Image: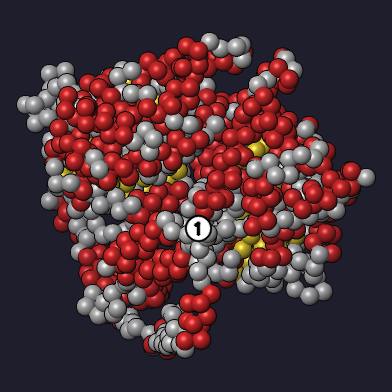
């Protein structure tokens, strides 16, 4: 009765629809896709080090 | 998702204040008179059914 | 949207009431209303005050029936009409309470949607009789080796966790809940304990941390959390254990085994005190109303190992009482001590001493004894009790620091190592199948030799070693649950082998 | 796999003990242990490489 | 609402009004009796029926004439909130008692406000380091937490809070609320002056702090709702501004105490020790209106005047329940001359864990606790017979512990006047290191006096040299 009237009038006559994405963007974390951080490189290329290590390292006792 | 859920709650409390506005409208009208008559006759039917 | 359906439901509640009982509020204040009228009124009835406040009714007087509000009186006002619900207080009880935090009236306060309820029940339900009870014979392993060894937990037993304020007080209990993950995850329904943690008087933040901890260990998938935060009404707090009990009874009734932790009853007593003194009931002993013993006893006696004709049901209870200043002669602690079947005294000094979990083994008893202790674990820990008792006596003499004889120092040396053996890391219970070896080693004195400092290292390593080699043996300890001659020999050899690491 | 590599690694640590010198052997072992332990923790860390476009 | 009444009774500051019309204000509505002392604000607390409410009076009631006209202001007292509060000292009513005239009001909010829900809770995990060694070592604080202090009030208790304000609140920045329930007026004036001096209040500019002050001269009833008022100011920051705040409460014993005074007059059967039966509820409600919601995180500091320094007293006991960390400060440790006087075996935090502050910190703390507990254990034996009659092994422990005890004193810059020693703040990273070394006895070879009243390990080393000369 009064319930119905209140229900009918309020519900019918008051309609909402969700807010714009732009406003939403403000309230959320936006995200710009992560890049590739690093491209690895050759592992100590050149026998300069290698020759040094082969000759230098021995450390054997008598 | 978090803002979406928040927005549903926000919509509900916004629409709640519209209920308050509507409440003031109903109690202003001679619906204030006419629905009292409806309630009155409803009590007649109900209490007579007792 | 969701709003349109909700409004439709709201429109869908109409239909006049005939209000067969009315009464007018008059004296209202302190949250305790008193209404004049209500000629028909059941005792303990729930009455809806016209203001959307519901209050149970605890005093019926030939003037004014005293209806204790479950809400705040800032929504109540003088001369309101009250309409009797016509139902004595009741809660939804069901399987859906698993994985849900619920407030006293069964509203999900974690808001994981409406509770899937298979029934409703009533707050007061009489305790299981002598006839429908069968003797306890089902272990419950808390994964705290000291607890399992010294004060074994079974099903249908009530054992009181008592000790100084929040000395990780909640955490001692929480460990038990956590170790029940091992069986619970398991599909053995005859070893399924559904766990109900009841939190009375704690702040929302404390509760929230706890439920989070439970979610972290992913144990909330078998937990029911009944909560009554400190904000919530003193009547609701008073009603809170009793409605937890009924929730437990649904499990118990189904025959499914369960365990209910009632943490802390000490705040129930404060609540009942407030309630009684504003029901103007004559002040009881130590200001706690004199019928608190009855209140607590009826609550506690509803956990039991029901008979085999009653499908071997068993709600198990663990009450938790905070002792204010460790006063064990205080009326509320004294009352509870009598009711329960065990004491699990926690001592602050030993906590500070770094014995965590902290248990004063002299003030800890299990009057329901080793009928619920694992048979294997009984064999290994057989003289553990004697050793510890000897250690206590020896330690007292040792304080005087008189030149101790070798016999006293055999005890002293053994005892020191045992104490270090007992210690365990909080929030990390250990599997019983792998606690039996550790106790074997200690009791068979292999650790007595091993230096005190590296006992902790040894323990870790020993487990790794048994995992490496004697994992066949570990499987057997789990599987056969009694150490046979072969197991005893295997275990003896393993320990001996690991003496020198 | 990673365990094969590491079994040879630890076997050689106790072998390098056997013969004289081992002054820089353990440093080789250390580099290998470090990064081998990093990739296993990485591989266990591995989240789904895409959002839930089904569920979420 | 304009509801005339007459004053039926004036039993203490618990006036009873008898409304003559059948429109009756609800409980927690507010009434103004206008007098040549201006308005007196009273708050409905019981309805005693027959159109006779009984109201707590939040202002002094001397001079009232029975039957005096009352008018009902209606609803809970509405304070004024905003950022305009920052740079004001406000009375219980909300009057600007720092006399910067009318506060520019935005929203005026009811004093009583229901505590946020279980769902709204958000659990903390932040480390907040104060640079106070004893705090850092024993029980680290956290942002959003509820911090707790116990002992004699303003016997060093007030000073401790002042040190906390000095350290935490400049680093924190943003909104901060100081609410002082029943504090010594002169001490409050000192705080006001000091705050203005340290620019936190800059009255020429803007102030990022707001102040609520309730003097201990204020009537008991007034003191009861000083707290609720402050919490509202905090809520505006917590919720509406949504920026992390700070909150100081000193003493929350005064909140309980005030309630106990009014309780008797109100007509309640006294509970044990004499405390109000609504002690549990009132404390509970208050302490759940101070919390870290998902809306905002409010670090709160609560100061408990323990009466007679008996923790077993029910009001301090129920306070201990609602705190997230406590650092009970003991008169005995004060007698030992250690300022800060925090008892080291009676401190706890849920933030002291081997996950939260890592195993190394936890290990360091474990050893400190064990050492000190041993030292406490041997106190009997020490008194009855000499320390030389203790075991040699124990004598090392005792010597170490005596050093640890002395080491724990950290001069405070706020107490610089009193100590006469320039204060020092030591890093959390530094603290763990300093204690670690001492525990390994590295620097144990230099006098106890060297460790006495000085800062970090490096300072101790230097102070040994100072003594050596």
Residue E344: x %, y % from top left = 65, 38
Which residue is rendered at x = 33% and y = 45% of the image? C464
- The residue nearer to you, when weighing C3 against E450, is E450
Displayed quadrant of residue E311:
top right
Q: Is residue E177 above or below residue C263?
A: below
For disc 1, the neighbor class at 10 Å (few under 14, some 14 to 19, many from 20) is some
- The residue nearer to you, when weighing C264 against C288, is C264
Q: Is residue C263 visible?
A: no
Outermost residue to the right: E469
Q: Is residue C218 above or below residue C46?
A: below
How many circles with numbers are drawn on the protein? 1
Residue E24: x %, y % from top left = 51, 50
Which residue is rendered at x = 70% and y = 44% of the image? E442
Outermost residue to the front: A62
Displayed quadrant of residue C377:
top left
Which residue is rendered at x = 12% and y = 51% of the image? B49
Instruction: Tell which subunit mark 1 falls on.
Output: E
Residue A21: x %, y % from top left = 38, 87
Left or right, C300 with respect to E115, comes to left
């Amino acid at each position: 009765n009064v319930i119905q009237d209140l229900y009918l009038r309020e519900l019918k006559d008051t309609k909402l629809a969700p807010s714009t994405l732009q406003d939403a963007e403000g309230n959320v974390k936006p995200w710009n896709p992560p890049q590739k951080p690093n491209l690895p490189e050759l592992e100590l290329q050149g026998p300069e080090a290698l020759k040094a290590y082969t000759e230098q390292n021995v450390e054997t006792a008598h | 998702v978090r803002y979406e859920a928040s927005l549903r709650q926000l919509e509900q409390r916004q629409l709640a204040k519209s209920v308050i506005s509507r409440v003031q409208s109903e109690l202003g009208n001679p619906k204030f008179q006419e629905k009292v008559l409806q309630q009155s006759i409803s009590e007649i039917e109900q209490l007579l059914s007792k | 949207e969701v709003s349109s359906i909700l409004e439709e439901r709201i429109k869908g509640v109409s239909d006049e009431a005939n209000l067969n009982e009315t009464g007018r509020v008059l004296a209202v204040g302190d949250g305790i209303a008193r209404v004049f009228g209500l000629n028909n009124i059941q005792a303990e009835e729930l009455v809806e005050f016209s203001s959307g406040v519901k209050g149970m009714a605890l005093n019926l007087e030939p003037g004014q029936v005293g209806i204790v509000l479950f809400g705040s009186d800032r929504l109540v006002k003088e001369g309101e009409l009250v309409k009797r619900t016509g139902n004595i207080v009741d809660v939804p009880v069901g399987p859906g309470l698993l994985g849900r935090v619920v407030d006293a009236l069964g509203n999900p306060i974690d808001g994981k949607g409406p509770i899937d309820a298979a029934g409703r029940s009533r707050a007061q339900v009489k305790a299981p009789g002598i006839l429908p009870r069968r003797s306890v014979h089902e272990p419950v392993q808390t994964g705290l080796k000291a607890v399992d060894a010294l004060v074994p937990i079974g099903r249908g037993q009530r054992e009181l966790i008592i000790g100084d304020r929040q000395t990780g007080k909640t955490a001692v209990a929480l460990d038990t809940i956590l170790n029940q993950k091992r069986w619970n995850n398991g599909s053995d329904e005859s070893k399924k304990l559904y766990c109900v943690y009841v939190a009375v008087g704690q702040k929302r933040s404390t509760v929230a941390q706890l439920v989070q901890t439970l979610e972290q260990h992913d144990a909330m998938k078998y937990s029911i959390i009944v909560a009554a935060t400190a904000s919530e009404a003193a009547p609701l707090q008073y009603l809170a254990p009793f409605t937890a009990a009924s929730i437990g009874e649904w499990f118990r009734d189904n025959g499914k085994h369960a365990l209910i932790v009632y943490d802390d009853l000490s705040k129930q007593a404060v609540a009942y005190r407030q309630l009684s003194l504003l029901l103007r009931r004559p002040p009881g002993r130590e200001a706690y109303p004199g019928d608190v013993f009855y209140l607590h006893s009826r609550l506690l006696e509803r956990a039991a190992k029901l008979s085999e004709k009653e499908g071997s049901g068993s709600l198990t209870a663990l009450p938790v009482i905070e002792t204010q200043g460790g006063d064990v002669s205080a009326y509320i602690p004294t009352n509870v001590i009598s009711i329960t079947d065990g004491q699990i005294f926690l001592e602050a000094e030993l906590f500070y001493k770094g014995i965590r979990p902290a248990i004063n083994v002299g003030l800890s008893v299990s009057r329901v004894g080793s009928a619920a202790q694992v048979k294997a674990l009984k064999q290994v820990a057989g003289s553990l009790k004697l050793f510890l008792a000897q250690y206590r006596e020896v330690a007292a003499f040792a304080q005087f620091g008189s030149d101790l004889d070798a016999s006293t120092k055999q005890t002293l040396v053994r005892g020191e190592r045992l104490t270090q053996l007992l210690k365990q890391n909080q929030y990390s219970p250990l599997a019983t199948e792998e606690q039996v070896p550790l106790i074997y080693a200690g009791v068979n004195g292999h650790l007595d030799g091993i230096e005190l400092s590296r006992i902790g290292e040894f323990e870790s390593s020993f487990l790794s070693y048994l995992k490496s080699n004697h994992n066949e043996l570990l499987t057997e300890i789990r599987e056969k649950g009694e150490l046979s001659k072969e197991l005893l020999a295997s275990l003896k050899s393993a320990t001996e082998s690991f003496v020198a690491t | 796999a990673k365990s094969a590599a590491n079994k040879l690694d630890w076997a050689k640590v106790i072998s390098s003990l056997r013969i004289t010198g081992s002054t820089a052997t353990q440093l080789s072992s250390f580099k290998k242990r470090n990064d081998e332990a990093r990739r296993q923790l990485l591989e266990l860390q591995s989240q789904p490489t895409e959002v839930d476009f089904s569920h979420y | 609402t304009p509801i005339t009444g007459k004053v039926t009774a004036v039993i203490g500051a618990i006036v009873d009004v008898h409304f003559e019309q059948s429109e009756l204000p609800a409980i927690l509505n507010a009434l103004e009796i206008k007098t040549p002392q201006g308005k007196l604000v009273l708050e409905v607390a019981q309805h005693l029926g027959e159109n006779t409410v009984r109201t707590i009076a939040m202002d002094g009631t001397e001079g009232l004439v029975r039957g005096e006209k009352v008018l009902d202001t209606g609803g809970p007292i509405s304070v004024p909130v905003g950022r305009e509060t920052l740079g004001r000292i406000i009375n219980v009513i909300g009057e600007p008692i720092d006399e910067r005239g009318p506060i520019k009001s935005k929203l005026r909010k009811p004093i009583h406000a229901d505590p946020p829900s279980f769902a709204e809770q958000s659990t903390s995990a932040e480390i907040l380091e104060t640079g106070i060694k004893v705090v850092d070592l024993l029980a680290p604080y956290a942002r959003g937490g509820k911090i707790g202090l116990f002992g004699g009030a303003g016997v060093g208790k007030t000073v401790f809070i002042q040190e906390l304000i000095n350290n935490i609140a400049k680093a924190h920045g943003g909104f901060s609320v100081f609410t002082g329930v029943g504090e010594r007026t002169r001490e409050g004036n000192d705080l006001y002056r000091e705050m203005k001096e340290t620019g936190v209040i800059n009255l020429e500019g803007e102030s990022k702090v707001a102040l609520v002050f309730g003097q201990m001269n204020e009537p008991p009833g007034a003191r009861a709702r000083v707290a609720l008022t402050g919490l509202t100011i905090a809520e505006y920051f917590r919720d509406e501004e949504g920026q992390d705040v700070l909150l100081f409460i000193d003493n929350i014993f005064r909140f309980t105490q005030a309630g106990s005074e009014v309780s008797a007059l109100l007509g309640r059967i006294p509970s044990a020790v004499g405390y109000q039966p609504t002690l549990a509820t009132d404390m509970g409600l208050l302490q759940e209106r101070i919390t870290t919601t998902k809306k905002g995180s409010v670090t709160s500091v609560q100061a408990v005047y323990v009466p007679a320094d008996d923790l077993t007293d029910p009001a301090p006991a129920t306070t201990f329940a609602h705190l997230d960390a406590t650092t009970v400060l003991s008169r005995g440790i004060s007698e030992l001359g250690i300022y800060p006087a925090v008892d080291p075996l009676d401190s706890k935090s849920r933030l002291l864990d081997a996950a939260v502050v890592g195993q190394e910190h936890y290990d360091v703390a474990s050893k400190v606790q064990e050492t000190l507990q041993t030292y406490k254990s041997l106190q009997d034996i020490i008194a009855i017979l000499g320390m030389d009659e203790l075991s040699e092994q124990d004598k090392l422990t005792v010597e170490r512990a005596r050093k640890i005890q002395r080491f724990l004193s950290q001069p405070f810059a706020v107490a610089e006047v009193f100590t006469g020693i320039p204060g020092k703040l030591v890093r959390l990273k530094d603290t763990v290191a300093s204690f670690k070394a001492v525990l390994e006895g590295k620097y144990d070879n230099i006098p106890e006096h060297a460790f006495y009243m000085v800062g970090g390990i490096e300072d101790v080393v230097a102070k040994a040299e100072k003594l050596a000369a």
